[PDB]
Image (cartoon, coloured by chain):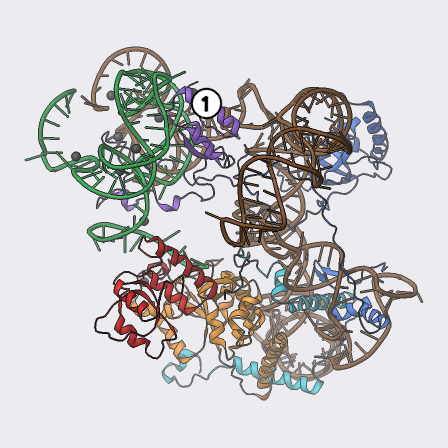
Chain colours: A red, B cyan, C orange, D blue, E purple, F brown, G green
Amino acid sequence: GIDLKAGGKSKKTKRTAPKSDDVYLKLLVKLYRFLVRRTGSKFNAVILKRLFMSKINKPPLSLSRLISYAKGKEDKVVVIVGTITDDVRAYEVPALKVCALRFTKTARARIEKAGGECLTFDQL
Amino acid sequence: VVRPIKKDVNKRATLKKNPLKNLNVLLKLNPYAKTARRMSLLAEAQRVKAKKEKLDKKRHQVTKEEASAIRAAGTSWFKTMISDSDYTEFENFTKWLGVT
Amino acid sequence: QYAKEYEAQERELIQLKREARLKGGFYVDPEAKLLFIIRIRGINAMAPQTKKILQLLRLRQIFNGVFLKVNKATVNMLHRVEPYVTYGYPNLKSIRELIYKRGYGKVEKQRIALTDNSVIEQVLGKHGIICIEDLVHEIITVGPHFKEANNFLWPFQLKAPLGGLKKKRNHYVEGGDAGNRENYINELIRRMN
Amino acid sequence: AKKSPRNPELIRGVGKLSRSKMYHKKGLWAIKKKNGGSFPVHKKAAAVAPPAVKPPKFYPADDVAKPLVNKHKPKPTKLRASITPGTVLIILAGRFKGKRVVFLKQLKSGLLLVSGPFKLNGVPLRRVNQAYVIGTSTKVDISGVNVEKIDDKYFAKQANVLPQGKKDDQKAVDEALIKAVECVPELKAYLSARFSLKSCMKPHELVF
Amino acid sequence: AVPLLTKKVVKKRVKRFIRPQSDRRITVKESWRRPKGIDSRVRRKFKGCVLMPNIGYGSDKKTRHYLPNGFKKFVVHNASELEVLMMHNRTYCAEIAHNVSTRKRKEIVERAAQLDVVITNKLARL
RNA sequence: AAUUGUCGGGAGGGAAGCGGAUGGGGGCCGGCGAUGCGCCCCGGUCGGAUGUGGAACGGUGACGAGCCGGUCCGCCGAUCGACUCGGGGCGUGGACCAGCGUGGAUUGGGGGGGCGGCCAAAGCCCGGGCUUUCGAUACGCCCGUGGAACGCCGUCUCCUUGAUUGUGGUAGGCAGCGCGCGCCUCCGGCGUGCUUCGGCAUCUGCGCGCUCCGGACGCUGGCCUGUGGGCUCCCCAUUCGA
RNA sequence: GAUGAGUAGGAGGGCGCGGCGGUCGCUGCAAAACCUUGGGCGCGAGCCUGGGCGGAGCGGCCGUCGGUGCAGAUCUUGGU
Ligand SMILES: [K+]
Ligand SMILES: [K+]
Ligand SMILES: [K+]
Ligand SMILES: [K+]
Ligand SMILES: [K+]
Ligand SMILES: [K+]
Ligand SMILES: [Mg+2]
Ligand SMILES: [Mg+2]
Ligand SMILES: [Mg+2]
Ligand SMILES: [Mg+2]
């Protein structure tokens, strides 16, 4: 015998692929698997890991909070693995380059009217 | 931005050979083993030849006076090594122990 | 250079002993700085402290072997598990044969056979150890980087003794196998490697 | 061209001389001096362009696996020291089991060429595997026996009737062998008699 | 057809794993069932008792599911399904389904002979 | 299905049944186990340019131009190629099972040699002195750089053997080393440096090769419709277990 | 590369039965069911197939659903 816990095997479980059956999400996962393998970029690894997560683990971000966090960084492309919702409490919308898994219709309309763009992760 | 593609990562594991049996593996791990073996074999052959010829030299590492000093020191050390106690501390067992 | 150094140390020890005898005094040999520890009991019915110490020594299987630098902390740790192990002072031949025949390195927590000097280099090049002989010298001399080199060595998986054991339930002093058997560990290593 | 080896082998794979002595003996210094302090550079041999193989008539649906290279090459079979030309051998297997025969030479394939002689015990010129033979201490002169023209090809099948040429060759070979045998007294009877184990005879104790 | 397989087929066990006591009670069938009884000696693996299957008996992946002839089985119900093996005749053999009529079996056999596809039961219903 | 009769095989000293290993007998199996391949000669069929026209069409481009391209049909030259077409030659070749050879891995034995440590062994022997005994003719002590042969321990090496086994399949890699690129009188010798005076990875480069070198290859035989080979099937016997 | 015990208990991947929406098939040149010291595949649940009998239907695959898997319950009914 060998004095090991569970024969030296791991007892922690983590997501290794999306549980969803969305074909577009699967294609994005393939894209970022390739990117992670052939680039070794920490950002790409984080994106790939978040692509696996469940709905509650990909909470939405409000438009007002996005504007607040993008203050002074409007030249950078803001990336969120999740949904971006509109906020009726936000009055002035600047021109923002935003990439997300999905945009609500109102949020997309406001972002496009303000002069920004809404991007998908392949475009990113 | 992709790093160069890799094709020679999936190499089969090299079979482990004991360096103590086969020479090439030992030399690969330690090249000086070749020289060590050569010198050992040559020294053994020279010693065997000297023994067989019976023409061996008369080598004295230590001179006569220091050899005598060494012998005296060794004799004294042996004398103290084999020495015994007087057993005089056991007065009640003096007769039994053969002291008197 | 290492081979010359070993020969010089042996000659110096012999000369020191002879000179001490000539002067009429005594020469106290330097205390062993290195030990080899072999587990001789199984993993059944283990007391908590003994089990924890045996894990800390990396002895999880019967007849596993590991080197251990001599220290008050390490010696006191070994004193608690004495009944479960036997240990002594390994020879140069013992160390060399162990590393050559059963030496496995730990790279990224994996067990890789030391079939090339590159395996040793990849882990211990920062410390100047780039070859098998360098590793042997570091282990035997307990050099400044002994800890890293020793941890790099996977615990040795030794076979059952060729001639068997005497009695593993008793100390070596009583005629058993447990405990410090000092220079006689080398013959046991011969039979176990 | 050097007529003698520069570095005799103490053992297999180890030379008697070191790299410095080998440098001195090989004359690299002389070559450098003659060439002007620099070794002469030799161009790499040009590879032969592959022949224009005609296009295949068929295309397999599967990629056949090419075996990996094996760097080990077989060496010639060793001949036991106890077996030397003229040694008497005991056959332990086959239709001639127990027969005592004279050893002539070892062939290229490693098999042993032996003769009865044919007249004495009916054993012709034949090949016997060394693993099925015992070499004894009895030796007979075979210097006058000529078997140069006989080789492994002499016994090759051409695929019932023994040609007369083989009989004549066997007679010619056996004439000198019998002449040599007659010198040793009682050797004729010894070769005409088979070996057998009687009661309380232990193979591991017989010296042969 | 020359089979592509080269490694020899090795079976770790050729005996069936018969249910315990199926020899004793007629109502207990042979098909394997793992005992769950608290005292079951078979479950406890007492020596000299009925052996239980486990993953350790698994066949080598290279020779797994290979028939003794060196090919793998594929069931074909008509000649149209036979052409699927046209490019796999060195690894796959065709077995005609048990319910196919003799008339269709002849056509399947002829087509396979044309395609050099091995049929395991080409003599059935002849 | 339980259960029962008949016929046939088999077993049975106070249960039977069952797990593992062989064997006897039976039953079954021909994808159970091949006969092809390459190079030539003869004969028979079918087609043969990068040339010139026609039919439809494609890749790319921008379902434009331009460039490039295949299929089919008809012609002038070219006189070649193919055939699971036939005949004749040379070479080579299959599945399974054994024997043998040379080696790799792992492993258990046998026979030697060198060196070192010890009271710098102890003892024994050779000479120079001292000592003088009861198990009566001993125990003995040291002087020599005196001489052979051991003992134990450690260490470095050579040779020779039996057993199990070959996992992988695009690499001439890695390591070590020979021959040529100089000569002589060729068991070897000749140059520069450092040496403990033995020697040294100090000069050590190229081309061609060799090996204990990134996991087994080679030769031979037997047999192929047989009273052969195989078997996970069946009935039994035996050893162990139960 | 390391590693392998498991009652109560948890979970994953699979096997099997009967319908529904689709799809691909089989069948009087013989379907289902049943029978068989015929053969084979899978560690296994099971699966594929030879032969027989039977004489009119049946199956594979993707989803989806359920009155869906027995050795026991002094279990039920029937039979012996
Ligand atoms: K039953
Ligand atoms: K289990
Ligand atoms: K072998
Ligand atoms: K259907
Ligand atoms: K059946
Ligand atoms: K269904
Ligand atoms: Mg282990
Ligand atoms: Mg106890
Ligand atoms: Mg019945
Ligand atoms: Mg229902």
Element under disc 1: helix
- Res B66 quadrant in image: bottom right
At which x and y percent is residue B56? 77, 72
Q: Observer-nearest residue: A12 or C153?
A: A12
Looking at the image, can residue C58 be seen?
A: no
Q: Observer-nearest residue: D8 or G37?
A: G37
Q: Is mark 1 within 8 Å of ligand 4?
A: no
> From the image, which quarter does the N terminus of chain D lie in?
bottom right
Q: Is residue B76 above or below residue E117?
A: below
Looking at the image, can residue C123 be seen?
A: yes
Q: Which residue is at 25% across, 65% downward?
A: A106
Q: Is residue E59 above or below residue B86?
A: above
Q: Quadrant of ligand 4?
A: top left
Which amino acid type is marked by label 1?
Glu
Would residue D187 be found to the left or right of residue B34 on screen? right
At which x and y percent is residue F217? 63, 44
Would residue C170 be found to the left or right of residue F67 on screen? left
> From the image, which quarter does the C terminus of chain D lie in?
top right
Q: Observer-nearest residue: B5 or C21?
A: B5
Q: Is residue E54 above or below residue D117?
A: below
User: Which residue in the protein does label 1 denote?
Assistant: E107
Q: How many marks?
A: 1
Q: Chain of mark 1?
A: E
Question: Could you classify mark 1 by the number of other residues whose Cα lies within 10 Å: few (under 14), some (14-19), or many (20 or more)?
Answer: few
Q: Is residue B55 above or below residue F101?
A: below
